[PDB]
Image (cartoon, rainbow over all chains, first blue to last red; front, side):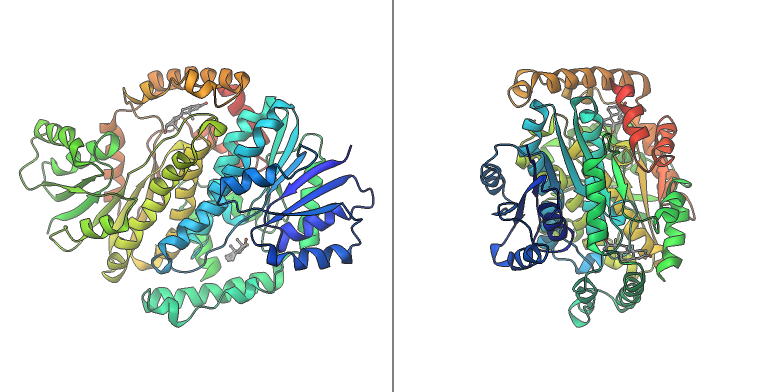
Length: 284
Length: 284
Ligand SMILES: C[C@]12CCC(=O)C[C@@H]1CC[C@@H]1[C@@H]2CC[C@]2(C)[C@@H](O)CC[C@@H]12
Ligand SMILES: C[C@]12CCC(=O)C[C@@H]1CC[C@@H]1[C@@H]2CC[C@]2(C)[C@@H](O)CC[C@@H]12
C-alpha cells in the first residue's frame, strides 16, 4: 500500500523538512508519522506542511519522548497501519563548550537522547521489521560522528556511539532483510544554530581563560564553516530519500564530500596524530 | 618526585595488572592509586601485589564509583600528593546479546559507566593537569571502539563514544601540554569472559529463534578468536607503559596488529558496505 514512515525529532531541522518532504511527495506513496517531544512545537511542521500542500492524512503528529520507553511504546501503538516501513531515527541534542563546563545532567541528556533514545526506538521497532523480513531504518549521522571536533566532546561521543551501534546491528541485519543506514550530515543551514554558539561569562566561570579563549576561537571558526558550507535541509532531506529508495542501501550516505578529505587522513593514520594535527590547525 | 597515577576499574583485568605492574616497577618511580567500585573485590589486587612484591606505600586502594561524581570528587581528594601525573580511565562494562534482549537499565549502565563515567573523571582531573601544564591521561580502548561487532551494539557504542570523546579533547589538549591517548585492546585473556558468553533460555524469550541462533553462532566465533588471539594482561599493560613514557604520545596505541587489516578495509570504504560484509562472513 503506502510506505509507512515514522520520524523522530520533527519539530525542526532535518526531521521537519524530511517529514513534510515525504508527506508532500507528488506520488503520495508515503504515510508519515512526525513525532516531536513537545507538541507545542508542531507549529512549524504544520505551516511547512501547508506550504508544500501535503494532502490531508499524509501527515500525522505524535508526541514521542525518546527518553521514555513508555512514550516510545505508546507512539508505536498510534501507528494505525500496525506497521512501519521506514523508521527515521533523527531526534538528537547538541552540546558545545569546554568539557569541564558541561553539566553532568547535560552530558547524560545528550547520550540518553542521542544514543539510548535511538536504542529504545530500535528495540521497539526492530523486532517486527525482523519478523516481517523487511523494513528500512535511517539514522541521522554527522561528520562529528566520524571525526572528533574540539568542544563537541560529548556531542561527538554520542554521534560516534551511533556509528558503533548501527555498524554493529548492520552486521547482524544483513541477512535479515532489514536495512540500516546512517546519513552523515555536515553543517545544515540553521539560523538558530549559529546563534546557539556564543556563551561568554557563564562558560568563563566554569573554565580557564586559555580554554575559554580557544572556545571563542572555535566558535569563530564554526561560524565561517557554516556561513560557507551549510547545506539546505531540502538538500540533506533528499539524501534520506535516496537511501530510502536504494534497492541495496549502503551502511552510510554522505550529504556532502567537503569533509571526506579530512576523514580519509583519519584512517590514513590509525594513530590519530595526523588528524588531531590537521584538525587543530584547521580550527586554530 | 614520584609519578602519581590513578587508575579506575582495578578489581580485575587490565586495570588490576597495570596497577601492580606500575607499583611493582623495580625503579619504584610510580605511586599508584587503584580505585575499585566495590572494595570487597580488592583481594586479587592485593594478592597480585604481594606476588610482584610491590613495596609498601607504592599501592593505595580507593573506593571510586565512576557513576557518581561525589565519589569521583572524594577519591580525587584522597590523593595525598595533591596531584595526579597519570590518570588511567579503565573502568568499563561489557554487554553481549540481541539489542531487543538488553534491558534499558543495562544499556544505560554501560554508557553511564563507560562514557559518562569517563567524562566525570576527565572533568574532575583535567582542570589541574591543564593548569599545571602537564599530565598524561590514558584511556582503555577496544577494537570494538574502532569497528562494530554483532551483538555488541551497546558495548561498541560506548567504545565508539570514547573514541569520539578523546579525539575531540585531543584536538584541544595538543597545545595545552596534557597528553591523551587511547589504548586499543583486542581480546585480553580472561577465563571469566569466555564464561560470560552463554545465555540460552533467558535470551531466547527476549528475541526470535533466528537471531538467537546467530547469537550462539557469534558466541562460538568469539570463543575461537579468544582461545587463539587473547593477549596476556601483562602484555597489554606493557603498552600503557609504552604510551605513558613516550615523549610525544600519539592519540592511540594498538596492543596488537591482528585487527588492523580489518580496520583499514573500514576506511578503504567509507560507505561501510565492505566492512559490514567482511565482518559478517568473518563471524558467520
Ligand atoms: C567540525 C566542523 C567542520 C571542520 C572544523 O574544523 C570545525 C567545525 C565545527 C562545527 C561543526 C563543523 C561540521 C558540521 C558539525 C559537526 C554539525 O553537525 C554541528 C557542529 C558542526
Ligand atoms: C570483534 C571480535 C574479533 C573479530 C570478530 O569477527 C568477532 C569477535 C567477537 C568478540 C570480540 C573480538 C575482539 C575483541 C573484543 C572486542 C573484546 O574487547 C570484547 C569482545 C571481543
